[PDB]
Length: 164
Length: 164
Image (cartoon, rainbow over the protein chains, first blue to last red):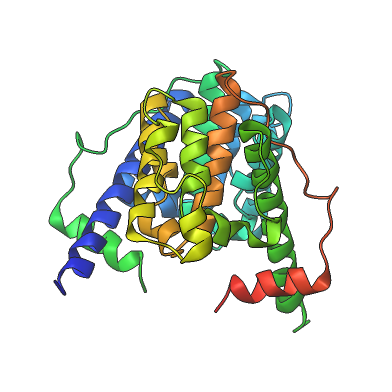
């Protein structure tokens, strides 16, 4: 009975990993390049490069690839996050505003850059996917709730990450 | 400078009130009846009656108006929530699953019944609205961010509610 609030927690972690995995595959399907491992996707979206590319994918008229800061992430891999990376997240936000995705789904720059609330970012990706799909601008995102598994260590890691 | 994290907080509350107002009007537009005041909408969705009605509106195959418990909410007005109201929320959930709304957006029964996380409910309504609109089953939800105002007292009440 007391272990219920300890197993339900395991479930949340698992479900979030599935949603992450789904976001990862869909972005890859759209971008045509590999994204970091599902287990490291959150940290891998922080510099906003992938998001800005996603923006270019559906709203090219608003997000030019040549104007993305550290497009190859060489700077990021080398020194880490830089204040200028924030512009990338903003380009993505502008991309979504251009195509009509309702703002209630938008995360704040800090939510992704300072990783204050990455889940909010994932949820937005998912909503953007549903919106893009209905406009016939991107493939449908997958649903992997039960077809995908993760090691006990990964669920455990995600669990503690979703708490403290 | 210290009042920034106290004004930004005011903004969040305001934004949420706008989202609630938008969900309220859209549901009314779909249902053809009045819903409680935007300021009391959250508490007013707890018994799931309006949600089940929303369910019947887009998936009558799954939700029969006659199988909604306390459809007139007479029980509710008399005595508060009753365990049997939980079924209404569940009918709404089944409605969404039937039309194919991605599960990532679904709140848990407890989130709305025990009011553990009503915002999750509101965000789901918005995703549902976006989806239903693309299916041509319902009118488009409005964007009221700037067009609408609330009293200071209301912004304030919502603010403290969104914290402790």
